Image (tube, rainbow over all chains, first blue to last red; front, top):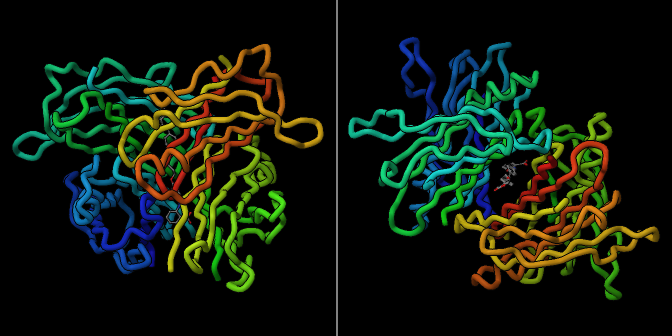
Length: 115
Length: 114
Length: 115
Length: 114
Ligand SMILES: O=C(O)c1ccc(-c2ccc(OCCCCOc3ccc(Nc4ccccc4C(=O)O)cc3)cc2)cc1
């Protein structure tokens, strides 16, 4: 599938499990429209967000709910969430993986784009 | 100086200079209102964004214009911008430094609160 | 298998392919003894370094040959290599993944340890 | 001051204070010879390690004692230490800053050469 998210926890040295992810797509009126959502599995991966057909060209926001993750673990973090904003599929369909590493005061994201 | 932003370039091994940064505060109606802005200096740092008097508790967004930065170097980047969204909290320490490390397909951010 | 390495390239937004990895284990005389080696695949992953039986307790060094990687791409990087040094299997067998993100002047490593 | 080390703690959102750092230079016989050492300050930085006169071209190793740092906070970390190994090269810029970001199971390092 063309959009996947994988999250690691740098404190525990583990997949980040049960991380909620909401994806938005910029609409014609310039608002963020809800596009897809899900949560990471026991492997820290989130599969099945969308399909090739539905994942059209656009500007997408992948919101990773890092505060809700840290608060569900009873930890007080810094950030409200991690925001990944990117233009997708503007040269034809690609497959996008958003990889994230989380600590309470830091996060890091990288994109792996394949054709 | 309660808020400082520092931006580094992981490709060239340098400060990220002349990067535009826009800070917003979340208003009561959930909209982002402009709060402060600037360009990073030769050291990749942006000082003097706000004062202790103006910088009250609440949710702030720091938007870093990474796309223009990369395109000026002739590099096509992945992100439209980098975003850092956080709550400022008078409990605990007073000075927030937001540090960003940039690559064309990656951004990392950490907070140093002292 | 109990020791895996996965590497991403933050410049290209791709797996880091053909990255050489050498693993060492501290011997009784305190020298670094060669233990296993390999290179990342087209997926940026390196599987098959060792076995449960051979991967005994010890202090291991995973050397990721980042300079050779960047130089094979004709790019001049900063670091000679990335070094991951850790005690393994001291509470029983675990499975270790060393995840790395590379840029010419930076690198990042995280460990995912499962039981 | 051609070489500076700065260390940050991603768990607490603070400088990593009183972290021991040992710098070595590679000798002709491939052994690591002591070169300079220190503890990070209250700002998490370590200044005054060397001078331009002593810091000649060659391969250097910066070893950061992250394991003691974490254990003093009551945290069992993954790494025995962090290592940064690099060639110092008079071609191009003169001042090397080695920045490290620490978590118990992760370390990241970037170089800023100006
Ligand atoms: O004050 C100052 O001057 C100053 C200077 C520099 C600073 C830094 C230094 C280093 C970082 O490092 C950035 C974070 C590290 C990169 O993150 C990632 C590491 C590993 C992976 N890997 C994966 C994660 C999930 C799934 C799969 C992978 C994989 O296959 O590799 C992704 C991102 C950030 C800031 C801070 C302050």
